[PDB]
Image (tube, helix red, strand yellow):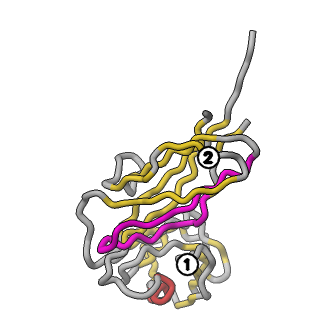
Protein backbone atom coordinates (compact mmCIF):
# COMPACT_ATOMS: atom_id res chain seq x y z
CA UNK A 1 0.00 0.00 0.00
CA UNK A 2 1.53 3.33 -1.23
CA UNK A 3 0.84 6.90 -0.24
CA UNK A 4 2.06 9.44 -2.77
CA UNK A 5 0.60 12.46 -4.43
CA UNK A 6 0.65 13.51 -8.08
CA UNK A 7 1.35 17.34 -8.37
CA UNK A 8 -0.58 19.47 -10.89
CA UNK A 9 2.63 21.11 -12.09
CA UNK A 10 6.39 20.41 -12.37
CA UNK A 11 7.41 23.77 -10.83
CA UNK A 12 5.83 26.89 -9.32
CA UNK A 13 6.71 30.48 -10.20
CA UNK A 14 6.08 32.70 -7.21
CA UNK A 15 5.58 36.51 -7.40
CA UNK A 16 6.92 38.08 -4.21
CA UNK A 17 5.03 41.41 -4.84
CA UNK A 18 1.89 39.22 -4.88
CA UNK A 19 -0.11 37.27 -2.30
CA UNK A 20 0.63 33.65 -2.98
CA UNK A 21 0.52 30.84 -5.58
CA UNK A 22 -1.63 27.76 -5.84
CA UNK A 23 -0.66 24.17 -6.42
CA UNK A 24 -2.95 21.25 -7.20
CA UNK A 25 -2.39 17.87 -5.50
CA UNK A 26 -4.13 14.80 -6.76
CA UNK A 27 -4.62 11.50 -5.05
CA UNK A 28 -5.50 8.98 -7.80
CA UNK A 29 -5.56 5.76 -5.80
CA UNK A 30 -8.75 4.27 -4.35
CA UNK A 31 -7.95 4.88 -0.67
CA UNK A 32 -7.79 8.11 1.39
CA UNK A 33 -4.51 9.63 2.48
CA UNK A 34 -3.09 12.49 4.43
CA UNK A 35 -1.17 15.16 2.52
CA UNK A 36 1.60 17.00 4.33
CA UNK A 37 3.34 19.92 2.75
CA UNK A 38 6.32 22.08 3.45
CA UNK A 39 8.63 24.60 1.81
CA UNK A 40 12.42 24.12 2.11
CA UNK A 41 15.75 25.91 1.41
CA UNK A 42 17.60 25.63 -1.85
CA UNK A 43 19.48 22.80 -0.01
CA UNK A 44 16.29 20.89 0.98
CA UNK A 45 17.69 20.95 4.59
CA UNK A 46 16.32 24.05 6.41
CA UNK A 47 12.65 25.42 6.35
CA UNK A 48 11.79 28.30 4.03
CA UNK A 49 9.87 31.41 5.15
CA UNK A 50 6.67 30.19 3.44
CA UNK A 51 3.71 28.15 4.62
CA UNK A 52 1.24 25.83 2.89
CA UNK A 53 -2.54 26.15 3.61
CA UNK A 54 -3.54 23.61 4.56
CA UNK A 55 -0.29 22.00 5.87
CA UNK A 56 -1.92 18.62 6.73
CA UNK A 57 -5.31 17.18 5.48
CA UNK A 58 -7.29 14.13 4.34
CA UNK A 59 -7.89 13.73 0.62
CA UNK A 60 -10.36 11.03 -0.47
CA UNK A 61 -9.25 8.61 -3.20
CA UNK A 62 -9.97 9.64 -6.83
CA UNK A 63 -9.79 13.28 -5.71
CA UNK A 64 -7.93 16.67 -6.10
CA UNK A 65 -7.36 19.73 -3.98
CA UNK A 66 -5.61 22.96 -4.46
CA UNK A 67 -3.05 24.19 -1.93
CA UNK A 68 -2.04 27.77 -1.21
CA UNK A 69 1.66 28.63 -0.88
CA UNK A 70 2.35 31.93 0.90
CA UNK A 71 5.66 33.63 1.55
CA UNK A 72 6.03 34.62 5.17
CA UNK A 73 9.28 36.50 5.53
CA UNK A 74 12.82 36.07 4.20
CA UNK A 75 14.96 38.36 2.07
CA UNK A 76 14.96 37.87 -1.73
CA UNK A 77 16.99 39.65 -4.41
CA UNK A 78 14.91 42.07 -6.41
CA UNK A 79 16.96 41.44 -9.56
CA UNK A 80 17.11 37.58 -9.85
CA UNK A 81 15.35 34.30 -9.22
CA UNK A 82 15.78 32.50 -5.95
CA UNK A 83 15.09 28.73 -5.77
CA UNK A 84 13.14 26.89 -3.15
CA UNK A 85 11.41 23.55 -2.77
CA UNK A 86 7.72 22.58 -2.15
CA UNK A 87 7.41 18.96 -0.86
CA UNK A 88 4.28 16.92 -0.65
CA UNK A 89 4.26 13.78 1.47
CA UNK A 90 1.48 11.21 1.36
CA UNK A 91 1.03 9.95 4.97
CA UNK A 92 -1.47 7.16 6.01
CA UNK A 93 -4.72 8.18 7.91
CA UNK A 94 1.86 -12.06 14.77
CA UNK A 95 1.00 -9.30 12.13
CA UNK A 96 2.94 -7.33 9.65
CA UNK A 97 1.70 -4.19 8.16
CA UNK A 98 3.63 -2.17 5.63
CA UNK A 99 3.43 1.22 4.02
CA UNK A 100 5.22 3.09 1.27
CA UNK A 101 5.19 6.81 2.00
CA UNK A 102 6.51 9.18 -0.70
CA UNK A 103 7.66 12.78 -0.75
CA UNK A 104 7.50 14.43 -4.22
CA UNK A 105 9.53 17.67 -4.40
CA UNK A 106 9.10 20.50 -6.92
CA UNK A 107 10.88 23.72 -7.57
CA UNK A 108 9.62 27.05 -6.44
CA UNK A 109 11.17 30.04 -8.22
CA UNK A 110 10.72 33.39 -6.53
CA UNK A 111 10.66 35.71 -9.56
CA UNK A 112 10.69 39.42 -8.55
CA UNK A 113 8.52 41.62 -10.85
CA UNK A 114 11.75 43.37 -12.18
CA UNK A 115 12.86 40.13 -13.86
CA UNK A 116 11.04 39.92 -17.16
CA UNK A 117 9.68 37.41 -19.71
CA UNK A 118 10.44 33.69 -19.50
CA UNK A 119 13.73 31.80 -18.85
CA UNK A 120 13.59 30.32 -22.38
CA UNK A 121 13.26 33.81 -23.85
CA UNK A 122 16.84 34.34 -22.87
CA UNK A 123 18.31 30.85 -22.21
CA UNK A 124 20.17 30.97 -25.54
CA UNK A 125 22.46 33.63 -24.05
CA UNK A 126 24.32 31.05 -21.93
CA UNK A 127 28.00 30.70 -22.72
CA UNK A 128 30.02 27.54 -22.69
CA UNK A 129 33.74 27.57 -22.37
CA UNK A 130 36.46 25.09 -21.63
CA UNK A 131 37.86 25.18 -18.06
CA UNK A 132 41.01 23.04 -18.10
CA UNK A 133 39.55 19.57 -18.95
CA UNK A 134 36.00 20.42 -18.02
CA UNK A 135 32.92 22.28 -19.40
CA UNK A 136 31.71 25.56 -17.89
CA UNK A 137 28.23 27.02 -18.46
CA UNK A 138 28.20 30.76 -17.66
CA UNK A 139 24.79 32.32 -17.27
CA UNK A 140 24.43 36.06 -17.86
CA UNK A 141 20.77 35.97 -17.00
CA UNK A 142 18.60 36.31 -13.89
CA UNK A 143 16.92 32.94 -14.35
CA UNK A 144 17.98 29.47 -13.30
CA UNK A 145 18.80 27.46 -16.38
CA UNK A 146 17.27 24.05 -15.85
CA UNK A 147 18.88 21.98 -18.49
CA UNK A 148 16.66 19.43 -20.07
CA UNK A 149 19.40 18.49 -22.70
CA UNK A 150 23.14 19.20 -23.07
CA UNK A 151 25.60 17.88 -25.66
CA UNK A 152 29.00 18.90 -27.13
CA UNK A 153 29.76 17.68 -30.66
CA UNK A 154 26.64 15.52 -30.44
CA UNK A 155 27.92 13.66 -27.37
CA UNK A 156 25.92 13.77 -24.18
CA UNK A 157 27.18 15.53 -20.98
CA UNK A 158 26.81 13.70 -17.58
CA UNK A 159 26.20 15.58 -14.27
CA UNK A 160 23.72 17.99 -16.00
CA UNK A 161 22.89 20.25 -12.98
CA UNK A 162 21.02 23.61 -13.28
CA UNK A 163 22.79 26.98 -13.50
CA UNK A 164 22.00 29.61 -10.86
CA UNK A 165 21.14 33.20 -12.01
CA UNK A 166 24.22 35.31 -12.83
CA UNK A 167 26.44 32.36 -12.02
CA UNK A 168 28.23 29.35 -13.48
CA UNK A 169 28.29 25.58 -13.15
CA UNK A 170 30.81 22.98 -14.27
CA UNK A 171 30.46 19.69 -16.10
CA UNK A 172 32.47 16.63 -16.92
CA UNK A 173 33.50 16.85 -20.56
CA UNK A 174 33.15 13.49 -22.32
CA UNK A 175 36.70 12.86 -23.77
CA UNK A 176 36.71 14.48 -27.30
CA UNK A 177 29.14 22.96 -31.00
CA UNK A 178 27.38 23.00 -27.62
CA UNK A 179 23.68 22.24 -27.84
CA UNK A 180 21.04 22.52 -25.13
CA UNK A 181 17.40 22.90 -24.19
CA UNK A 182 15.64 23.94 -20.94
CA UNK A 183 12.50 22.96 -19.12
CA UNK A 184 10.04 25.86 -19.62
CA UNK A 185 7.74 27.36 -16.98
CA UNK A 186 5.04 25.00 -18.29
CA UNK A 187 7.22 21.93 -17.76
CA UNK A 188 7.60 21.49 -21.53
CA UNK A 189 10.95 21.67 -23.37
CA UNK A 190 12.41 24.76 -25.05
CA UNK A 191 13.56 25.33 -28.56
CA UNK A 192 17.12 24.17 -29.20
CA UNK A 193 19.96 26.56 -28.41
CA UNK A 194 23.49 26.18 -29.89
CA UNK A 195 26.89 28.01 -29.70
CA UNK A 196 30.59 27.24 -30.24
CA UNK A 197 33.35 25.92 -27.80
The residue that appears at 68% across and 53% down in the rendered structure is 63
Q: Quadrant of residue 112?
A: bottom left
Q: Nearer the viewer, mark 1 or mark 2?
A: 2
Q: Earlier in the sequence, mark 1 or mark 2?
A: 2
1 and 136: which is toward the camera:
1
133 and 90: which is toward the camera:
90
Mark sitting on residue 184: 1
Chain part drawn in magenta: 7-29
Q: Quadrant of residue 2?
A: top right
122 to the left or right of 102 = left
- The relative height of residue 116 versus residue 158 in the rendered view (above or below) is below
**Where residue 176 sits in the image (x, y, percent)?**
61, 76
**Where residue 173 sits in the image (x, y, percent)?**
55, 70
Category of crowding for the residue at label 1, using alpha-carbon neighbours closer than 10 angstroms: few (below 14), some (14–19), many (at least 20)? many
Task: Check disc 2 and report the residue beneath it.
Answer: 59
- The relative height of residue 167 versus residue 126 in the rendered view (above or below) is above
On the question of residue 72 being in view, the answer is yes
- Helix, strand or loop at label 2? It is strand
- Helix, strand or loop at label 1? It is loop
89 to the left or right of 6 = left
- Tell me, yes or no, whether the highlighted magenta stretch contains residue 25: yes
The residue that appears at 54% across and 59% down in the rendered structure is 66
Q: Which residue is situated farthest in the top direction here?
A: 94
Circle 1/circle 2 CB separation < 8 Å: no
Category of crowding for the residue at label 2, using alpha-carbon neighbours closer than 10 angstroms: few (below 14), some (14–19), many (at least 20)? many
The Cα–Cα distance between marks 1 and 2, rounded to whole angstroms, is 30 Å
Amino acid sequence: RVFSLHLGATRVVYNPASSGETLTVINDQDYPMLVQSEVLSEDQKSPAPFVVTPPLFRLDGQQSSRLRIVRTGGEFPPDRESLQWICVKGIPPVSLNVQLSVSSCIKLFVRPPAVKGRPDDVAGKVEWQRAGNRLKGVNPTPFYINLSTLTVGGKEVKEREYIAPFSSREYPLPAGKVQWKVITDYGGTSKQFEAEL
